[PDB]
Length: 549
Ligand SMILES: *[C@@H]1O[C@H](CO)[C@@H](O)[C@H](O)[C@H]1NC(C)=O
Ligand SMILES: *[C@@H]1O[C@H](CO)[C@@H](O)[C@H](O)[C@H]1NC(C)=O
Ligand SMILES: *[C@@H]1O[C@H](CO)[C@@H](O)[C@H](O)[C@H]1NC(C)=O
Ligand SMILES: *[C@@H]1O[C@H](CO)[C@@H](O)[C@H](O)[C@H]1NC(C)=O
Ligand SMILES: *[C@@H]1O[C@H](CO)[C@@H](O)[C@H](O)[C@H]1NC(C)=O
Ligand SMILES: *[C@@H]1O[C@H](CO)[C@@H](O)[C@H](O)[C@H]1NC(C)=O
Ligand SMILES: *[C@@H]1O[C@H](CO)[C@@H](O)[C@H](O)[C@H]1NC(C)=O
Ligand SMILES: *[C@@H]1O[C@H](CO)[C@@H](O)[C@H](O)[C@H]1NC(C)=O
Ligand SMILES: *[C@@H]1O[C@H](CO)[C@@H](O)[C@H](O)[C@H]1NC(C)=O
Ligand SMILES: *[C@@H]1O[C@H](CO)[C@@H](O)[C@H](O)[C@H]1NC(C)=O
Ligand SMILES: *[C@@H]1O[C@H](CO)[C@@H](O)[C@H](O)[C@H]1NC(C)=O
Image 1: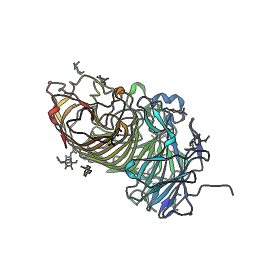
Image 2: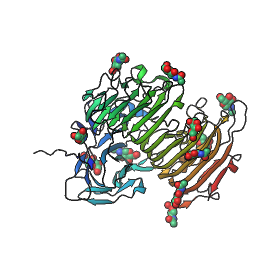
Image 3: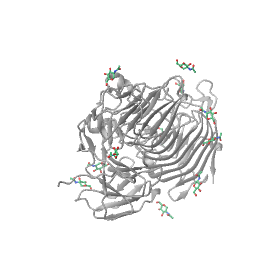
Image 4: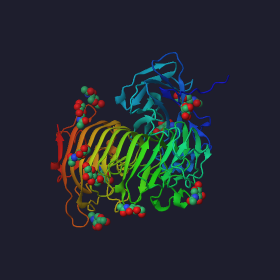
């Protein structure tokens, strides 16, 4: 009979397919269709490896502009595309990647490079041995003959990326069990009524769903759980109306914003927002009441966000906290596609971020984020804590691998650790005016450890002390190489700042750097400037920046 995909559904491996897959690299796909990679084929086999059968795993594809040519102006203008595949496993597995029959053999580089997964080449295919881990893995497979140079940094990156998201099975806390109370399971196609349903749980089983570019998933006040099953592909954006103790989004399905134009404004027919009013449609949105709420986000893959990925509405955001795990953001080619907000007390781990703006937004206290892989695009720092002076303390960001960066100029506000200017006076974040800070606020007890920047990188830090800084520690940070000196994105700095109202000088206390390396060179106080390119620390703060060797 004619060939057909064969998927796995057993205790060791789960893969899925879409019969409405559409090969398309220039226009929007049909409402009920799913853009599929025409370049990469992926199959998975549970070890031990043998002549046994390999199971097909659907490879999704995201492209800049989502097929809307008039939206390309809102991207960086690169021709890069991003493909990815997800599967669940509970045992070591071999991932077999195949390109078309006419493609020549080419070695690959897996990022993060610290994974060191066994790789073998045979039968015009690439075999990667992915070990099982309860936290799973999220990595990039980069073919040497697919690398291109991104101007003006010259960064060497895949023209057609392929991401592999291997995740653990779903337990009863992330998957609606049989007999789950008061649930609703919409049929494939246009999804209606969720904004008025009396259901508590919305279940998206395998299939394709869409809300169009002029509506989104507004969930009624009774909905406290939305589930995206592995094999479910939902075109839309989520907004909870519930003010309950917990609102949750889980499952390993996909939530895609590809039908929305950049900066789509829900209050204006979803047309591009007027005057950068900051009302672009978020992929995750909620609204607080007068009581605490926890946002649990687990397993989901978000693709093609039309604006910031997430923000909660409310006068007091101190009552919201997040619990994020095994989550990914892909195909975020548009500008201002920020990573998630990590509200007070948040625990975020095992995440993959493709972002063209603020990545790890350190705006709240008692936050812990670890095991993150980031494909930083061309705008904003990897870590952001500028824009507005704040009282923030007790933060730990650990094990963050920035596998790529492609900045272009100083105006992009480049840097691994950055704090841009005050948004109220410098909307684009860059200004020589450093007298709008707040001497009455302090960011304290911050730890950024085990950060790794692969390939060419921007500056270690570009920090505006818009409020006092105290006890900030950088422990273990490796930069493989620096971007070109000519694009002015690699020199680190920290200018002296002053209080907006009384002119009191903002203070910096105990800012330590340890285990900082550039390529094969260890950075110390002696070569901090000449090799580490740290030459912009204000003389007033120089004595507060310590190199622990
Ligand atoms: C086959 O794959 C190569 C990359 O290996 C790609 O450049 C080429 O366009 C593909 N052939 C076609 C026409 O599908
Ligand atoms: C994509 O852009 C790169 C430069 O960044 C260029 O080398 C490559 O030829 C372009 N690909 C196509 C199909 O034009
Ligand atoms: C529910 O959402 C639909 C759009 O899908 C909208 O037309 C309708 O007015 C909404 N219902 C209410 C009560 O807001
Ligand atoms: C795997 O099988 C289970 C049980 O029949 C089913 O609920 C699930 O949808 C299947 N997964 C897929 C997408 O094939
Ligand atoms: C929060 O609002 C509810 C509903 O109006 C009310 O019953 C409750 O007393 C309020 N809680 C506080 C802290 O005032
Ligand atoms: C941080 O957690 C501590 C408990 O260790 C608590 O006292 C403090 O209020 C929290 N800070 C914020 C702003 O949530
Ligand atoms: C400091 O922050 C860490 C997180 O990095 C937290 O575990 C610890 O309780 C905080 N205590 C202080 C003030 O050092
Ligand atoms: C800096 O900006 C503030 C806020 O707009 C303004 O009040 C002040 O005059 C500016 N100072 C300089 C150096 O122009
Ligand atoms: C920094 O890396 C070294 C590698 O030898 C490791 O021993 C140390 O624990 C790391 N420091 C932190 C705080 O993770
Ligand atoms: C980098 O950008 C800053 C701010 O735009 C500017 O002051 C500096 O001169 C630039 N670096 C150089 C010397 O080109
Ligand atoms: C260190 O890196 C530089 C630049 O890549 C290279 O020229 C040099 O040979 C390297 N030295 C060692 C000992 O690896």
